[PDB]
Structure formats: structure tokens, C-alpha cells
Amino acid sequence: DQFYIEEIMGAKLLDFREDIEDITESADKQLKIRTGLDEINLYWNDMQFQFGIWGKRDVPCMLNGLIVGTILERLEEDQLQLSTFNSQRHVTPFKAEVENLIRTFSDVNDTLDMWVKVQKLWTSLEPVFTGGDIARQMPLQAKQFQGIDKNWMKIMEKAVETKKVIPCCQNDMLKDFLPDLNRKLEDCQKMLEAYLEGKRKKFPRFYFVSNPTLLKILSQGSEPTSIQEDFEKLFDAITKV
Image (cartoon, rainbow, N blue to C red; front, side, top):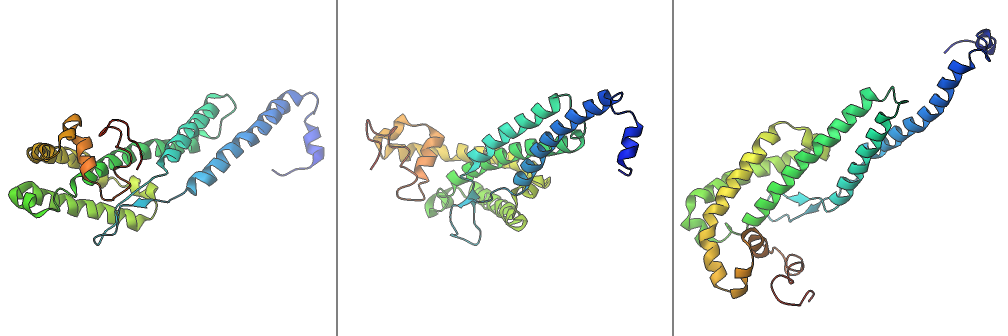
């Protein structure tokens, strides 16, 4: 990075324009691609973090991302762009950076997915054990659900502490818990069928509805919102009210 115009002509410009040229159009396209990585990094480190909370009705708050469609889709063409660059010949430098970047992106996805799925399971089972009688009548898994409530609240508070979902996913302890919690919640549903049959009896049309969607229907948590997307498969022709 240290000489004078004399020295660059010292190497013959026309004779070595082959080499200098390969580097020149290379370098201009490298400016293009380095921009393509810079600005995407600037945006992707500074992402939106807006989340929708179920409610504050206890000490903790439980939340979901209602923008996650944008996350997923823009992620998809992100990795498309990154592979598109890497496959091309003139992409020498980025390998050290880009792979790490892609790795994080790839990894964060499946962690998020597992997490949100477990949330849905929990988001079905909360109103079940609010009622007194059913909680009394089967104490064992009710206390098992007290345990999962403790662990789940701990996960939520760790996420609250982080303030950013990417370090939140980077935690390693989380990954062990999530699928075991999933399996246990399947066991809890396999306890709850015995009440589902009676609840189905109390109103006819639920016979033409499956189990987990019936749980979702029964965990309204709201007058308008929860059932507004399900009128179709419970009556003939009505869709909005």
C-alpha cells in the first residue's frame, strides 16, 4: 500500500495489463459483492425485534413473533444470495466470514422452529389445568405441568434477559430440554383424551373435528380472535361475524 505512480509504471503497464486487468474487473465485481455482504450484514445484525405477548396474567410474559413470515422468507433468499456468491469464481475472501454467517442463520432456524412448536403445545394446555376439578382429578400430570411451567418460565426469563433472539437461540442448554418437553406434552394429551370425549358429547359438531385442533378451539383466550379463523369447519357456510 506504499509507493508512487512511478513504481506502478515500473512494472510495464501494457505488458502486465493482463494480470492487472484480471485483478481490475475482479476488484470492481468484488466491490459489488463486498457491498452485497456488507449491507446485508448491517441489516441482519440490526433486525426487527417486535413480538406479540399472550398476556401478563402472572409474573411472566409469553410471546410469539407475528412477523416471522418475513424472517423465514428473507432468510431463504439470504442464503440463496450467499450460495450464489460462493459458487461464483471471484469470491475468494468471503469464505471465512460467510460460512459462519450462514451457519448461524441455518442453526437459528431449527431452534426457533422447535421452540415455537412447543409453545403451541403449551398454549393448548394452559386453560385445561386452570379449572379446579380436572386438576384435582388427575394430580400427577397436573404437578408435572407445574414442573414444566417452572422450567418454561425460566426459559422465558432467560430470553427476556437476553433481549435479542439470536444469543437466546445460541444457548446450548435449551436444546436438550425442548424435545423432552415435547414428548411429555404428548403424554399429557394422552391423559386428556378422557375429558375430550365428554366435552365432545356436550355439543354435536365437534365430532367432525380432530383432537389437537379441538384443543386449540377450546383454548380461546379471547372473544373474537381465536375462533375467527375456524368458523368454516364448524358450520356450513359462515365465515365472518
